[PDB]
Image: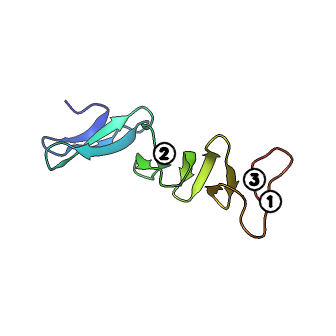
Amino acid sequence: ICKGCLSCSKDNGCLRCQPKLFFYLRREGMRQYGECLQSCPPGYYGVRGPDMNRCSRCRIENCDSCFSRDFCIKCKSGFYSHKGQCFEECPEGFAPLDDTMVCV
């Protein structure tokens, strides 16, 4: 009924996931239902909490895959990571490397 849960609520769904899974929120009714996932969806990154791990929307431009809120571990194929972000051309002060895609 709630899957991979440790406390399950008729209406808001799972409120505490089993240690290995990722809490994911979504709409059921106007309410927010909570799930417990194997890994996160797409556009979502893992977040190791002290109580529980949870999924969170990646909000970096041109980022294939976040690592934290402000830090992209993978920029869109063909894009220059710099200071967490992913950029078209390196900004004033910086330039790429010997085939890295990283501003200096």
Q: Nearer the viewer, mark 2 or mark 3?
A: 3
Give the SS element for disc 3: loop
Q: Residue at x 32, y 32 (%)?
A: 4
- First along the sequence among labels 1 and 3: 1
- First along the sequence among labels 1 and 2: 2
Q: Residue at x 46, y 43 (%)?
A: 43
Q: Nearer the viewer, mark 1 or mark 3?
A: 1
Q: Determine crowd level at label 1: few under 14, some 14-19, many 20+ residues with C-alpha closer than 10 A.
A: some
Q: Determine crowd level at label 2: few under 14, some 14-19, many 20+ residues with C-alpha closer than 10 A.
A: many
* Circle 1 residue: 95
Point out the residue furthest to the bottom here.
92
Instruction: Name the amino acid, label 1.
Output: Ala
Q: Position of residue 97 (x, y in %)?
A: 83, 51
Give the SS element for disc 1: loop
Q: Nearer the viewer, mark 1 or mark 2?
A: 1
- Count the labels in the image: 3
Q: Residue at x 14, y 50 (%)?
A: 30
Give the SS element for disc 2: strand
* Circle 3 residue: 102
Q: Determine crowd level at label 3: few under 14, some 14-19, many 20+ residues with C-alpha closer than 10 A.
A: many
Point out the residue furthest to the front here.
89
Q: Nearer the viewer, residue 83 or 13?
A: 83
Q: Position of residue 60 (x, y in %)?
A: 53, 55
Mark seen at residue 87: none
Instruction: Name the amino acid, label 3.
Output: Val
* Circle 2 residue: 45
Circles 2 and 3 in contact, beta carbons < 8 Å: no
